[PDB]
Length: 99
Length: 99
Image (cartoon, each protein chain N blue to C red):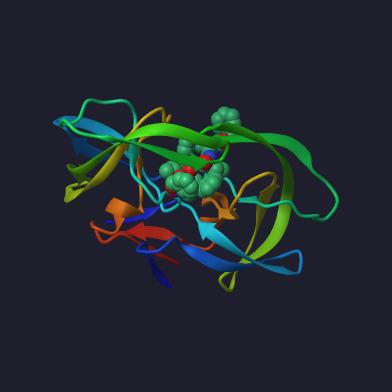
């Protein structure tokens, strides 16, 4: 679909069997979600943005549905206040910015 | 144009007579730029993201060219590490996310 920006670009995602909402975020190199258990194995990672850095857990090859579109990729989990779908997965779903 | 997300979505902007690069950021409610003098008058504001908050100066009705497209709107200036074009101006230029 084509999404407009009058409103925050929040879409439905499905991950680890749970339904969530997440921001389609062209300003995010990475995908970062609120705290959640995910299959087995992680390595430590840090991400920064406005305000500095947070420590997150990196999980690779995780399956996520984004507004119906399946993708498999790296998902970070940590103390973010909003679920964010970054360019890592946005690419896989064929997402472009158009104006 | 249609921009893809393999790479960060950095575009050329022109503001206050200066050429800069800025991120087309669907995850930004607001437009926030590195430190710079701008016509006269501001009011204090704070913005947060990953890592918490920063204090910025809010300037209204500022003219910016974004990749050739003129827009007039609110521009924040403060201690951001990257120039960010948020939904406030992205709307004005007709920017949509498509997948």
